[PDB]
Image: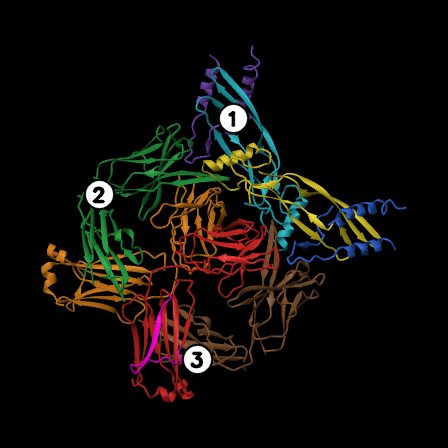
Chain colours: A blue, B purple, C red, D orange, E brown, F green, G yellow, H cyan
Amino acid sequence: PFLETLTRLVRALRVPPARASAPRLALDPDALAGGDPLRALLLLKALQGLRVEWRG
Amino acid sequence: PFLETLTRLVRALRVPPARASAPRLALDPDALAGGDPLRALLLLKALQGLRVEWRG
Amino acid sequence: SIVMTQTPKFLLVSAGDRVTITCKASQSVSNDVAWYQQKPGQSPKLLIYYASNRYTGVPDRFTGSGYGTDFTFTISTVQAEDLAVYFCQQDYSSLTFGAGTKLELKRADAAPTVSIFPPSSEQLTSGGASVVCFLNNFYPKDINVKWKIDGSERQNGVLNSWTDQDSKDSTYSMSSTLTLTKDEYERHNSYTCEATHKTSTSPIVKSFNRNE
Amino acid sequence: SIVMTQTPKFLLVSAGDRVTITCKASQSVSNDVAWYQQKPGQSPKLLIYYASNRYTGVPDRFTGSGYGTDFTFTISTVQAEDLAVYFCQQDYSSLTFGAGTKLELKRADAAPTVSIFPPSSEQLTSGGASVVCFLNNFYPKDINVKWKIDGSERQNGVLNSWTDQDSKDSTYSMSSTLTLTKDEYERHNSYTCEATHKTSTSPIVKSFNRNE
Amino acid sequence: EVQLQQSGAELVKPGASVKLSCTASGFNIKDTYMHWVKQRPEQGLEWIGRIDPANGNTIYASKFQGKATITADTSSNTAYMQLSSLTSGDTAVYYCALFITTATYAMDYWGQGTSVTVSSAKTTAPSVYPLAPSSVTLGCLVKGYFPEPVTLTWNSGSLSSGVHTFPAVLQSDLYTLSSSVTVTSSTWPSQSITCNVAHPASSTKVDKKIEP
Amino acid sequence: EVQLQQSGAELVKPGASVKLSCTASGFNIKDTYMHWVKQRPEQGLEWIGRIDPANGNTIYASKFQGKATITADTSSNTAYMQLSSLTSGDTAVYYCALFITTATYAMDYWGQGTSVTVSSAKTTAPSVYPLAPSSVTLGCLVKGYFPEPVTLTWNSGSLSSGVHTFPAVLQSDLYTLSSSVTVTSSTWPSQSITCNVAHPASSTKVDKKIEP
Amino acid sequence: DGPCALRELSVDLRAERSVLIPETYQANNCQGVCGWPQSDRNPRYGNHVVLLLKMQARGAALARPPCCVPTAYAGKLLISLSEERISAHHVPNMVATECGCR
Amino acid sequence: DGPCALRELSVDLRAERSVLIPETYQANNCQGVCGWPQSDRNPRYGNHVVLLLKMQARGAALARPPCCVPTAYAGKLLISLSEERISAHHVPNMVATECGCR
């Protein structure tokens, strides 16, 4: 309803690069192990991170 | 008068070995850097160390 | 586009000398450069990436340096297993692969070994005739070969082929072939193959006769 | 005293094989053993200490293992620069240096090159005469050499000398000398040097005549 | 480990199109891009284009635009390149590559190479001939075949010492090749020596025996 | 760095005594012991004894006790070994060594070797002779000298390709030696080739030129 | 190359279902060569390292010479976004931030 | 050899004039090879080391692979004896007592 639109927007903004050489490797995240108050503060953190990310 | 006799005794007790192969290297000590109450406690520490050393 | 100029285009060492190669750029390329190696009949293999690092398995002889617009690659002590062609690549834009530089070794002189073979029976039955001349294990590269029939010159139909420098003793080789028709072949009597080289004041001649 | 027995006493490889040597002890020697290498005409060099280690500059091919009363030393891929003699040393008591193991390579067969030289003028003036026969670049080791004067056998005064395996192409050599007095040398007319080897069904003979 | 496998050599008419393939192994192509490279005998290496399997965005050089289409399929880890509008100038060797270079790590993998030929001739089968004369030299001659690839061996691969094989030469839309072997004087005619020729395009295998 | 330097070869009468020396360089001998080692041509290595310069306590094997005295002097970093009561069985090569082996580090340094011979013969000077006949082989012969050490060179060291030098052989307390060189057919007699012989014991230098 | 110091090394984290924030995962690495006498910009060596270097200089041959390694670390936080669930995780000792050879 | 573990390394201290106590100076050092998966007896690896090991396993080629190094130290005290003066000194970070690869 709302979070899915945010996911779609995030995916849309991440446009592919146009450089002719690979910048670095890609590795899946699998083996470095560690009124809802969640969905409240987490989205604030996510937007704070996106603020810095988008400037690039 | 007294300390010199201790030095002579320490030198005498350190007899040379009879093994036919060199055990390890020798290196001079100028590599690493840091009613008298001195001559009162230092002698006690030295005797405590010699206690363990002599058993070999 | 960035254009990379590599020098020198040719080289020659004595198996104990030091070697240096330069690869200049046409525009500021930061420090994105790579040095490769390609032996005959094989795909290239990376030797040095970025500007100074070394790929796994590379010995300590090879090294490289440079920055900005000048890059150099040097080998300290050449060995007998370092016959190949070296390229320099940049990556700041669409990739470019330099021009390439060859390499050669040295050794003492030697003389060729000459053999001559006449046509076989099956080929004669077919309708043609071929005479073959092999020159083996000589040095240096330059040599001359001539054919003579019945004591006269002949320079039509000859085919020559050369070989690359050997990896075991660094010696060359060569093959020559002369082709004729059966009727023309059966009309003459004697054939000779002559070789001229640096290590002899007179030609080396090998001859054969048809009748015997 | 501790006695070390080393096996095998001889070896032979094909430049691409794996080699293993063992050095057993006569008493519990903990893990105090070292392995050396002595090339011809030089002083030894260390290769492995405390039964498993590597001195500075030792490549990855060599390795060693063992403990208690059995120790082994193995090379994976032999090369052409590994012709030497290997020893095993212990240190638990007065040092002992094993017995030593040799090593050899292989290659395709080849035939000898034969040369014969007569006596010089100065030597003839002196009062003696010496005839020399050189055999060069043959394989395998075994060969036979015979001298003949005026078509007869002669087996007195001959001297022979051999050469070690070459490090460039792995081939042997040999020299033979025959000594006589001036008058005895001048009494005869012809001399011949004959060589018998595996790679020929008939002997190779080189002859010369005194008159011309 | 990682391995790149490619197709076989191809010959096409002047005006058709080809589709080359490159399949990985022990790796996932989604991790990084795939590059296609071209090589000519004397013009040096060049760059054609690259593809990114994850998104499908491809990049081509400024010279190959409009006559080369690169596509990828991650269901089986494969990449294809379609080459169109051939003009007899594309006869060359093509390579499949993975490149990554960074200040702290790198990765470089290459294929094996696919050969592409453009001509309007017709396929044909070879003709094999033997040649017969303290050493002996023998030869095997292959004449009149098309296209280039062909394999020649001596004694089924059990004789690889002192053997020379000269490169092919083309004249009048037909190739030629020769091979020479040298042996000692005690292994012929006491033994059997044969030359084997295999042409895969026409599926022909021949063996010929040398006799005096 | 560390370097061990020794004396020269010595010849002694059967019944006298010898004093060998070994001097270090770039090191202090007080750090560790000094070992003396013996080697015979066919019996392998052996251990004689060791000395500790700091205190002066020395250790000898169980077989060399009573006929070998080891001393040290730290004012100039030198060690001496005195050998007494020679019996013509001590002709051998002697080495000066430093050994240290530990689970974490090690040191191993060897000298160059001093040769000791025991005989009752008399010194003598050599005699040099030349030997002259698409290749040519020439020879230089050295006859009738004592003791063993002698040096032979061609063109003062400017010709070291295709040259063989055979080992010395002893008969009737006199030695012999020969050397052979092979060159092509376009470098003789168009140039000059000479063999140089140097005997240090008698201080003799000779050069002989080969002529047809 | 130069002496022992810190240098960049980063990767990309990809998931087939969710989206991760941040994308580029940064984890530097220590690299270089440290010798005797010191010519660096990091703190002074310890006593152990100088002892080993002097042992090497005297003429010995160690079986494990000194190496440039990091000596500090920092944590990181990751966010995973997917329908019906947004998650956050924190992992310590991920990013190197200093170098010094031991 | 075995995996990354501690081992002995000692020297002797000599003076021309005074006498030092203790004589044999002990300063251990560790050696071995630490691989993936872990087969050791020390604490578990960090996240940085496992990241590097996975990067190596995937097919990459790092310019500085992980190494066995120490992570703890202890001090020592020395006594110098000579006529008219007996002295003592204390020096920290001399003896290695634990180690694991980073």
Q: Residue furthest right?
A: A35
**In the rendered image, which residue does mark 3 sit on?**
E208
Foreground residue among D183 and D145? D183
Q: Secondary structure at mark 3?
A: strand
The boundaries of the magenta stretch are C141-158
Label 1 crowd bin: few (<14), some (14–19), many (20+), radius 10 Å: some
Up-down relation of residue D167 to residue C197 (above or below): above
Residue H40 lies in the magenta stretch? no
State the residue in front, E122 or H34.
E122
**Residue appearing at x 17%, y 45% in the figure:** F124
Q: Amino acid at mark 3?
A: Lys
Subunit of label 3: E
Q: Is residue F120 left or right of residue F134?
A: left
Give percent across and percent down for residue E100.
62, 56
Which numbered mark, 2 or 1, is in the foreground of this view?
2
* Numbered badge on residue H22: 1
Q: Is residue F62 visible?
A: yes
The quadrant of the image that shows the C terminus of chain C is bottom left
**How far apart are the alpha carbons under marks 1 and 3?**
86 Å
Q: Which mark is residue F201?
A: 2
Residue F109, above or below B51:
below
